[PDB]
Length: 119
Length: 119
Image (tube, rainbow over all chains, first blue to last red; front, top):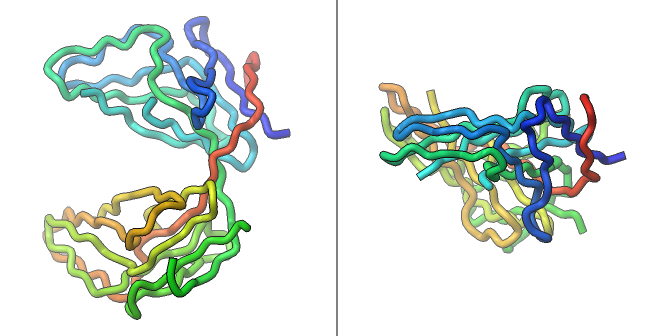
C-alpha cells in the first residue's frame, strides 16, 4: 500500500485537497486566523499531523510574504505549519481556510548512471 | 529508460562519484581551484551538463561555508555548480576535485490520500 494519511489535531484543521487537476500535491490550509505583523513573522499551523508513505518525503512548498520551507519524513509527528515572513509595512491577515502551502510527496530514486560525450 | 547522463564541458570536469554504499546521490566535484574570499561568495562550477531522467528532478544538495542550493529538471542545459558563501574571516580554497554537493534524483508521486483519526 502507498497511502498518504492526515489526522486532524483539532476541529480547526481543514482537509488537504488538490488545487488543480495538474497540481503537484495537495494544498495545506490555515487552521486559525493569524496576523503576521508588519516586518515580523509568525508560525501558521494547519493542526494536521501527517504520515507520508514509507520510504518517502513530504515537502512543504509555497502555495511581500515569504514562506519557510520544510521537508518531513515518515517519522514526523508534529503539527504541520509554515513560518511566514512579512517584509512589508502592513500586517498580513491569514484567515482560517486560506491556502498557505502545498504538500508534495517525493521519493529518491537510483537511476542507471552514464557519462556521455554531449547532451 | 531510467538513465541519468552527465557530459563533461571541459577536461577539468570530474565524473560523479557516489560517496558511500548508503548515499542518497552522487557527489559533485569542483572542476577548478576556487578561492572564496572572506565574507564573500563564489560560484563553483563542475563543468558538467546533466540530463536527468524524463519526468524527474535533480537536487543539488550540500554533501563556515553555506552552499546554495538548486533543483534542475530534464530541460536544464547549464553547467552544474553551487554558490558558496564564506562567512568567516579567512578565505576558503576549494581545490580541483573537492566534493561540493550531492546530486540526488527525485520524482514526485501521487499516493492514495486519506484522513485518519490519529496516527
